[PDB]
Image (tube, coloured by chain):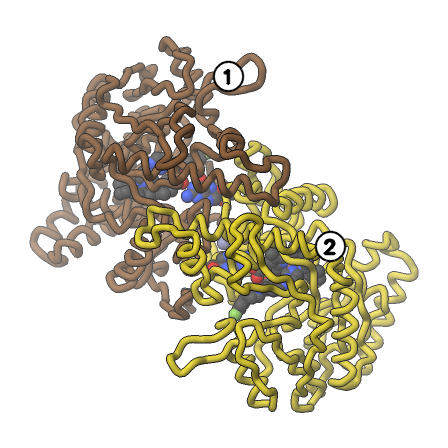
Chain colours: A yellow, B brown
Amino acid sequence: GPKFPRVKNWELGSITYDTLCAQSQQDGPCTPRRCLGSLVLPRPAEQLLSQARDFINQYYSSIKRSGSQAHEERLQEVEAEVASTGTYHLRESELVFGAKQAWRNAPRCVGRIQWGKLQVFDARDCSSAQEMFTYICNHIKYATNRGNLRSAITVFPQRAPGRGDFRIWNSQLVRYAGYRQQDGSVRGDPANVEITELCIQHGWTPGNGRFDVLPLLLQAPDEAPELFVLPPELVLEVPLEHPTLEWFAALGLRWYALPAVSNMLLEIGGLEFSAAPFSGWYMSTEIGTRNLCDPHRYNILEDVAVCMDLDTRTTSSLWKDKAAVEINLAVLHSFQLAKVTIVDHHAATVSFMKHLDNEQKARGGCPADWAWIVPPISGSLTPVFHQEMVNYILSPAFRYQPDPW
Amino acid sequence: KFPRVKNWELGSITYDTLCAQSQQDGPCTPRRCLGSLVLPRKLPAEQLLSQARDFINQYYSSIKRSGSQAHEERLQEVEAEVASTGTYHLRESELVFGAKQAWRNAPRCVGRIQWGKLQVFDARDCSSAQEMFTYICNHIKYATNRGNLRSAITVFPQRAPGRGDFRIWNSQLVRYAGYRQQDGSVRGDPANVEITELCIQHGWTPGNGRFDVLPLLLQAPDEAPELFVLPPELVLEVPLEHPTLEWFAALGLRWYALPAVSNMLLEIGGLEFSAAPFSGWYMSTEIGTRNLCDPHRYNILEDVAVCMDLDTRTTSSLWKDKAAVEINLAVLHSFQLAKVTIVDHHAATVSFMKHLDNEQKARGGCPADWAWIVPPISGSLTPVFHQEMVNYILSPAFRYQPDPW
Ligand code: HEM
Ligand code: HEM
Ligand SMILES: Fc1cccc(CCCNCCc2ccnc(-n3ccnc3)n2)c1
Ligand SMILES: Fc1cccc(CCCNCCc2ccnc(-n3ccnc3)n2)c1
Ligand SMILES: C[C@H](O)[C@H](O)[C@H]1CNc2nc(N)[nH]c(=O)c2N1
Ligand SMILES: C[C@H](O)[C@H](O)[C@H]1CNc2nc(N)[nH]c(=O)c2N1
Ligand SMILES: [Zn+2]
């Protein structure tokens, strides 16, 4: 056989070899001695030029003008630009290409079948926090599109030598408040206690509900962040009801439509875009299993099981399994009823296999994080469970970055 | 620089420093992570000697005698025997220690809380297929124990540089036949088509049901394997019914009580035992989810869905998830009613968490394969989902080896 990692599908018996991974410049957490793939937190002078060069080569290949005059001049242009300023800038269409390619490269995203259809908003002219808010609102309105959801990213100015970053402080554009109680419990989402307390320390008047939408804390270079409240009619939400358990609607559960990640760094050709929120549409277990059922999130499993009258006294009743199923169904059903785009874990992983097969033909491999791609309920029921995956970092990339506080 | 292992539900952090004792490489390297592969790709005398000394050291340490007369004299014994013969032999109590330690070290086993309670049968004085059979029968009898199962291992004679290995050709001691139909399909268990064909060809008379227990092919060194039918009365089986779905028993489903792995190689102190079958008791998802719902196994999810009257025509009705849940319920109910030891995936993973904790205290870590430990349904509903894990190879170890045909 060839000298590349052999990849196997155990449902179908079919083999592939990943040859893409040879183009991995940046290393991962693993050595020949121990496997750190399950761990969730994955722990320039001439160094910029070589990343830039390599990026410009990717751009040129993808437009098939590799080795052209236009290619060799762009490289010279980037040399010279780095030469006199320490940095360089991307052509509009270089940024569009880099953004889709960052998405294409993201090992943990299961929606990558869609990678080619990404609206890139170019917001590198933005010069204030107020202006970031407008751009974000535009993003929300465009991506939400009354429930007919549309992938999009907005790119604010790149990190710049010595001058401070644009940062959105919130981890998503839509997030519910988490209020620490005297009894030590939390009202709302325990995931958001810190950013809740920061919004208050920064003058937000806090509600006290279970599903208060957070204000955005936005930060322009070298300035304190500023608070912006989203006008409620921009933030589309779905009340959760269950197609047959009539009492589930009485639980007053809801979820927002737009999943928009706002604290990741987009790295292109060595340039770093510290503020570059992106959004897709939800895969249903992100809501019905993680957000509503994690013990450290809303944790509603016992409540739903009690209403369903299950024996919550014994693990072997499978009461957790039954409640989780019904919560996922409710989420699916309610987004359907509301006409808000959503995808179940079956449809999603099926499309993601199609994705793998496309990338196998197009680039000879596809970096994929098995733990993240396999859904949190019904694992071996989906085809990705039976698919081996190779995980590696390719650039352009979306990367985590330290919280700005 | 050591592995920092974090729990994402409780927020607590440990350090694995046990992996420092890993001598053998896993499928991973800096540039690409390979940990979701089922088979990692590979499937003088001082080498053997340092493995021996090392194991001998582990043993004496275990019994708190590390520097005794007994210790130094055992090391010279080992040394003298290797120098003169290129090999050596284990004392029965070292074997007992080695086998428990191989189980303890198995990264994929969720049952390791039990590791200290392992009945070890020394069958190293075996010399023919017939002797193998007798010992295998006593194993089954002992381990089965009328349904109150007990962990056991029987160890046949070690590989010898000279000659062919003792092998059990079956991958499990109890396995159902899979008969290929001239029209594509398989009657019985599709995972066993090959071993079913080999049995017929070495002259067994095949049945034609969905649940025909296979004979064993046992092979003494350099001989054609021989066929031994297990006497029905040793093979305890549990017919499947559901606590409330009355039609479910009509499905004529059943499964065997004894889960016994017979194709793995046991490596102690550099010695290799190519026939060393072991058994515990099932975790229910192995049967309810994988064996009966894998598409390429009994694949019964649609039949059940249709009896439950579900909307089969759409993924988003979650028909697969519902059916799977009841099928797993049926398995637990049925083993409980037959009074046959079983553990559901919630109890099992809770006890594996306790295990990691004991192991942290006792050894500074525990090798674990996240993708194997996390069950095939209801992942994030179990605490192991939320727990980071470090996979690495310690010896003594259970290993895969080539099929002997
Ligand atoms: C189009 C619909 C999309 C679906 C269904 C989807 C699905 C997912 C899911 C389920 C995850 C893992 C979330 C988690 O458990 O934390 C994920 C991660 C990710 N997605 Fe998407 N995604 C979509 C669109 C996008 C877009 C438009 C981008 C960027 C342009 C993107 C980039 C990412 C990245 C970077 C991650 C990993 C984030 C992390 O490590 O926390 N996705 N995706
Ligand atoms: C006491 C009850 C036990 C339970 C509940 C249990 C549970 C499990 C489970 C769920 C797996 C993964 C199985 C699969 O998906 O193929 C596994 C694998 C394994 N178990 Fe156990 N186990 C038990 C006893 C034992 C014993 C007695 C040994 C050996 C002495 C053992 C050694 C292993 C090994 C070596 C593997 C890896 C098998 C492979 O790679 O295919 N287990 N165990
Ligand atoms: F504290 C932490 C450290 C590292 C990862 C973590 C997981 C949260 C981030 N996962 C992204 C979740 C998320 C939310 C909304 N939308 C998306 N999204 C949008 C498009 N594709 C994915 N993804 C926590
Ligand atoms: F192609 C392959 C080659 C080797 C292993 C594979 C995985 C399946 C076998 N894993 C063990 C299954 C199994 C069955 C019964 N019992 C146990 N068992 C008993 C105690 N602990 C686990 N384990 C595929
Ligand atoms: C320890 C483990 O890596 C952690 O729970 C992971 C598992 N798989 C995941 N998968 C997705 N999609 N998202 C996550 O946050 C996680 N968390
Ligand atoms: C490709 C993937 O690693 C493969 O499906 C694994 C995943 N996890 C598993 N986990 C267990 N316990 N048993 C298995 O057979 C598998 N199969
Ligand atoms: Zn790895």
Judged from the image, the secondary structure of the residue bearing numbered disc 1 is strand
- Residue A22 visible at all: no
**Residue A55 position within the rendered picture, expressed as x and y whole percent measured from the top left:** 76, 63
**Residue A150 position within the rendered picture, expressed as x and y whole percent measured from the top left:** 76, 59
Q: Which residue, given by chain and number where applicable, does mark 1 sit on?
A: B180
**Residue B137 position within the rendered picture, expressed as x and y whole percent measured from the top left:** 21, 24
Mark 1 vs mark 2: tell me if same chain.
no
The amino acid at mark 2 is Trp
Q: Which residue, given by chain and number where applicable, does mark 2 sit on?
A: A115
Q: Is mark 2 within 8 Å of ligand 1?
A: yes
Residue A174 sits above or below residue A179 on the image: above
For label 2, the crowd category at 10 Å Cα-Cα, with few meaning under 14, some 14 to 19 and many 20 or more, is some
**Residue B330 position within the rendered picture, expressed as x and y whole percent measured from the top left:** 37, 36
Q: Chain of mark 2?
A: A
Relative depth, front residue between A129 and A257: A257
A159 sits to left or right of B98: right
Residue in view at x 48 percent, y 57 percent:
A38
The amino acid at mark 1 is Arg
Residue A223 sits above or below residue A297 on the image: below
